[PDB]
Image: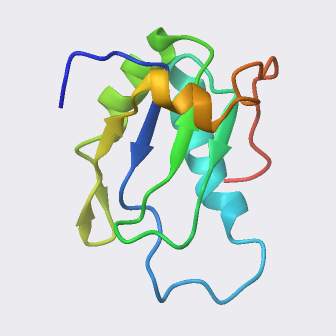
Amino acid sequence: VQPLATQCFQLSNMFNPQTEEEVGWDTEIKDDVIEECNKHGGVIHIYVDKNSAQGNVYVKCPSIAAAIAAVNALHGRWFAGKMITAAYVPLPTYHNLFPDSMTATQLLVPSRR
């Protein structure tokens, strides 16, 4: 919505409310946005929630530069019969919700796509 290039964003189409029937299913959806973010500028935090209304996820980078290119790549894709979107978070509120993920000194890596 607004010119707030923050180091964080949320997707809205990565799983469905009736499509989980293994345990461990976050690992792949997590791996996927790890690819995208890595190919741009890396990412130091991921949270795939599972009880979202519009498939929301929560991702955080070391630097707005990574966020810029990552969001720019992510929104406008097609999931399996949906449009991918992302939006940026309000940093001055996000930093209060994740008082710990602020310090995240460790770029994650994938396991398997």
Is 35 situated above or below 64? below
Is 15 situated above or below 23? above
Q: Quadrant of the N terminus?
A: top left
**Residue 74 vs residue 17, the one in the foreground:** 17
> x, y (%) of residue 55?
41, 65
**Residue 57 vs residue 4, the one in the foreground:** 4
Please indicate, yes or no, whether residue 35 appears anywhere in the rendered image. no
Q: Residue at x 63, y 49 (%)?
A: 47
* Quarter-of-image position of residue 101: top right
Left or right: residue 42 versus residue 12 is right
> x, y (%) of residue 41?
56, 16
Q: Residue at x 47, y 12 (%)?
A: 64
Q: Residue at x 45, y 83 (%)?
A: 17
> x, y (%) of residue 65?
46, 9
Left or right: residue 20 versus residue 103 is left
Q: Residue at x 65, y 90 (%)?
A: 21
